[PDB]
């Protein structure tokens, strides 16, 4: 019915979905891989968006981050990896995304997540935020904590894909 | 291919908050069932029949949504319905903790079922069924928070 209407996204059934999953991914962990695997199972396309210039100086640069993720996520056909240096809503808009994946680890974060969701609704109304709990197995891990365990020689082989574990050991002499 | 999501709840009764959640879910998944708990441990104002009838009318305009009672383990219901997603609205910090527990249990009971969480719109971020009832019970104006059909049925219950 194209000559009458192009269509609306609401009240008219299911629509093509394209999700961004933004983060610093410094580096990508198995907790991250789990989230995006889950989101890629239920949305048509997912983009792992890696922040170029995070406020705190990352251990891996963008080019390293992007490469490690690419490799770690290549077995998922509907996932692509991109760096970005914008608001997550502007990137979403540029990418013609309509879904924003957010991992939801801690109670302490829930307020902030809600507030950021409200900001994003104001910024890009047609962008929907969707929240995924982490697996029980990855509930206590973070990039930051894996890096600090690793610096002081703790075993983190369980928490990382192999390519990342190797890059990480190299960073730490 | 197909996504089919369950949105379970007591829905005693369905509010504008719930309607926002399911409108949003039904825009992202091919089909959505509103799943209404038959026998909540606290006895509801509206019985299952009424809760279902109300919710059906409020959601009639959504072509890929269907309202159903259920009185079994949600794992079994999702499995009976060939659902592969579970939708939860997430209003409060208090409710996050509990839903994260139920989610881990659901992962044990049904690995293939993915739990998914939406935040309420700002508009509806403070309303619950319980609160609308409380306010209405002492004659407060709650017309902004319910669809007409539910509004009239609530007024009737309180008279």
Image (cartoon, coloured by chain):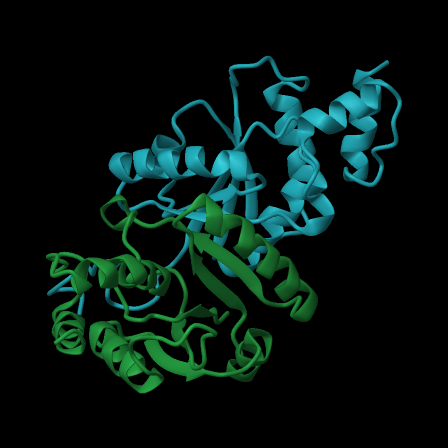
Chain colours: A cyan, B green
Image quarter (top left, top right, bottom left or bottom right) of the N terminus of chain A? bottom left
Q: Is residue B22 above or below residue A125?
A: below
Q: A114 or A71: which is nearer to us? A: A114
* Residue visible at 62% across and 65% down in the picture: B106
Q: Is residue B128 above or below residue A169?
A: below
For the question of whether residue A73 can be seen, the reply is no
Q: A84 or A39: which is nearer to us? A: A39
* Residue A129 point in image, percent of width and height: 40, 46
In the rendered structure, the answer to whether residue B146 lies left or right of residue B82 reads left
Q: Quadrant of residue A116?
A: top left
In the rendered structure, the answer to whether residue A154 lies left or right of residue B3 reads right
* Residue visible at 35% across and 75% down in the picture: B44
In the rendered structure, the answer to whether residue B1 lies left or right of residue B153 reads right
Q: Quadrant of residue A168?
A: top right
For the question of whether residue B131 can be seen, the reply is yes
In the rendered structure, the answer to whether residue B47 lies left or right of residue A77 reads left
* Residue B120 point in image, percent of width and height: 33, 50
* Residue B159 point in image, percent of width and height: 12, 76
* Residue visible at 48% across and 74% down in the picture: B41
How many marks can you see?
0
């Amino acid at each position: 019915m194209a000559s009458m209407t192009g269509g609306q996204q609401m009240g008219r059934g299911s629509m093509s979905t394209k999700a961004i999953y933004p983060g610093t991914f410094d580096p990508i962990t198995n907790g991250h891989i789990d989230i995006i695997t889950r989101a890629a199972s239920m949305f048509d396309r997912v983009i792992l968006a890696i922040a170029a210039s995070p406020s705190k100086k990352p251990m891996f640069d963008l080019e390293e981050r992007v490469a490690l993720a690419t490799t770690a996520l290549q077995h998922l056909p509907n996932v692509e990896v991109m760096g970005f240096s914008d608001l997550m809503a502007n990137f979403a808009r540029a990418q013609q995304a309509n879904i924003l994946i957010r991992g939801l680890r801690a109670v302490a974060d829930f307020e902030y997540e809600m507030q950021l969701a409200h900001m994003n609704r104001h910024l890009m109304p047609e962008l929907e935020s969707v929240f995924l709990m982490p697996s029980k197995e990855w509930s206590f891990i973070s990039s930051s904590l894996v890096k600090e365990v690793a610096r002081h020689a703790g075993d983190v082989t369980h928490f990382l894909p192999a390519n990342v574990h190797q890059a990480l050991m190299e960073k730490l002499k």
